Length: 313
Ligand SMILES: [Zn+2]
Ligand SMILES: [Zn+2]
Ligand SMILES: [Zn+2]
Ligand SMILES: [Zn+2]
Ligand SMILES: [Zn+2]
View 1 (cartoon, rainbow, N blue to C red):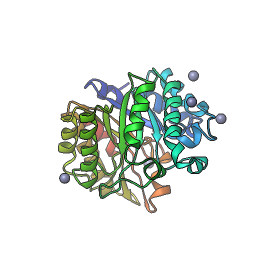
View 2: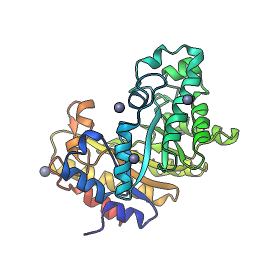
View 3: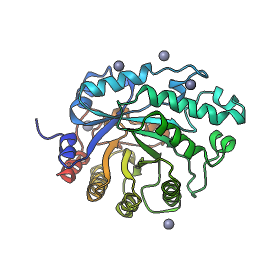
View 4: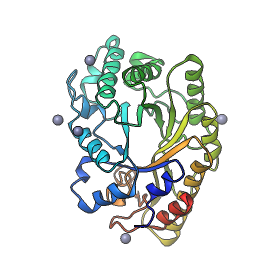
């Protein structure tokens, strides 16, 4: 047993984990690595609204529970994902009269947070609330509740579970720019108004060869605001097919990302959006792209894995 990524990360006060999904659990080879290589697990889909509250007022934590129990059995911490999001939302939510949505969102949050109280280290309370230019995404929540929905979601979560870290999660906020500035301002605003928020999750869905050079400065400025930071859905996709040069560039990128987190004391950990290309969500969403993870489809460790372990030391 050589030091696993999880072990290397823990030695430096951080976690290194992977997201997973119920359909993958039957794959014995996949689960054996998932349970021994990582120190943290993120529930990839079954904690989302379409699954936990398929019909109004009727909750279902069955699927999510399976993954949480599995993580506990391996002594792995767990991150909840995600409470409020414009995607993967059951159809009844749109039919809720505008004036009732705030109460519905608060209730959804209260039941889910309460059910898992004491079992999760973090909760991605609100996910992808901003557009690339920094303006608010015009989701059903933004449109019918207004700008305060985000703050209300965090207050509802904190009221249901006092100890769990509350995170705001979004993509394309790794580098300093319009989007991250908007998140930065919101966080600063929350701190001043006493709105509860403990961290910022940078999804980090990156492109090989295009890692934001201002990544670490960006992580640092958030840490200086008084919040923790985590890379929550890390993957670095490339245009297929793979080549030694592309794999090498990807390795360099993974190393740079890991190093960046290690230099900022409040960067608590890294989670890859699953760990093997075999189950990566990338191909299905980004036509012609893939090979974004440290393990390939046959579970062989890529140069990326070597770079990650070296960075973790
Ligand atoms: Zn069910
Ligand atoms: Zn259980
Ligand atoms: Zn209720
Ligand atoms: Zn700026
Ligand atoms: Zn291979």
